[PDB]
Image: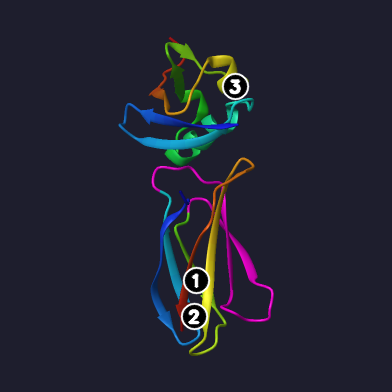
């Protein structure tokens, strides 16, 4: 199904969060992380993280707002189906 | 089309790759060497007896979904 799996928020504050995920055995070149207010107007914010990482900080959030967070994994021009979760600060 | 290959060191190390059938195996090898912290010259990668070249493709090699590449530490100069 999706790579990575077990995408979860492992710590948070009113304006930030720490997500973590699990690639299992897969070698990954990098991940693309997007995030935006669930049912908001804005385009998503986006950033990339190295393939060896399984953790990332998202900050500059606002208190009490729900975010849809999506992680995409890539290896040598293959992209797996992404995994998403929602989390309210 | 892409297949899953399992790369297994004597180590019992195990890394899975999603490789295009027509893509040179160089990136798989170098990725595995990098993740191991070991130089490329000190690895022998084998599929069914055959040492895998950087320029081999899974297609040239008859590889299929879930095939195993074995990796051994290679000593040179003997």
Q: Which residues are magenta?
A: A24-52
Q: Chain of mark 3?
A: B
Secondary structure of the residue carrying tag 2 is strand
Instruction: Give the distance between the C-alpha atoms of the residues marked 2 and 3, in whole angstroms.
Output: 44 Å
Q: Say if labels 2 and 1 share a chain.
A: yes
- In primary-sequence order, the first of circles 2 and 1 is 2
> Could you tell me residue A7's position as x and y percent?
42, 62
Where A59 falls versus B42 (above or below)? below
**Dot 2 corresponds to which residue?**
A16
> Could you tell me residue A77's position as x and y percent?
64, 42
Q: Quadrant of residue B47?
A: top left
Secondary structure of the residue carrying tag 1 is strand
A17 displayed left or right of B22 = left
- Name the residue at the front extreme: A39
Colour scheme of the picture: rainbow
In terms of depth relative to the viewer, which is nearer, B58 or B27?
Answer: B58
Question: Is the N terminus of chain B in the top left, top right, bottom left or bottom right quadrant?
Answer: top right
Question: Is the C terminus of chain B in the top left, top right, bottom left or bottom right quadrant?
Answer: top left
Number of the label disc, if any, that sits on residue B57: 3
Q: Is residue A28 magenta?
A: yes
Find out whether the residues at labels 1 and 3 contact each other: C-beta distance under 8 Å. Answer: no
> Could you tell me residue A78's position as x and y percent?
60, 42
Find out whether the residues at labels 2 and 1 contact each other: C-beta distance under 8 Å. Answer: yes
In terms of depth relative to the viewer, which is nearer, B34 or A62?
Answer: A62
Q: Is residue A88 magenta?
A: no
Q: Chain of mark 1?
A: A
Q: Chain of mark 2?
A: A
Instruction: Give the distance between the C-alpha atoms of the residues marked 2 and 1, in whole angstroms.
Output: 7 Å
In terms of depth relative to the viewer, which is nearer, B77 or B43?
Answer: B43
Q: Quadrant of residue B69?
A: top left
**Dot 1 corresponds to which residue?**
A57
Q: Say if labels 1 and 3 share a chain.
A: no
């Amino acid at each position: 199904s999706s790579v990575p799996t077990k995408l979860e928020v492992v710590a948070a504050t009113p304006t930030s969060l720490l997500i973590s995920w699990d690639a299992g055995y897969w070698f990954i070149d990098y991940y693309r992380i997007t995030y935006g207010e669930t049912g908001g107007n804005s385009p998503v914010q986006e950033f990339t993280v190295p393939g060896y990482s399984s953790t990332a900080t998202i900050s500059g959030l606002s208190p009490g707002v729900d975010y849809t967070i999506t992680v995409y994994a890539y290896y040598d021009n293959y992209g797996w189906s992404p995994i998403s979760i929602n989390y309210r600060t | 089309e892409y297949i899953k290959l399992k790369v297994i060191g004597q180590d019992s190390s195990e890394i899975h790759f999603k490789v295009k059938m027509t893509t040179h195996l160089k990136k798989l090898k170098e990725s595995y060497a990098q993740r191991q912290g070991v130089p490329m010259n000190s690895l022998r990668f084998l599929f069914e007896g055959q040492r895998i070249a950087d320029n081999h493709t899974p297609k040239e090699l008859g590889m299929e979904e879930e095939d195993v590449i074995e990796v051994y530490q290679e000593q040179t100069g003997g």
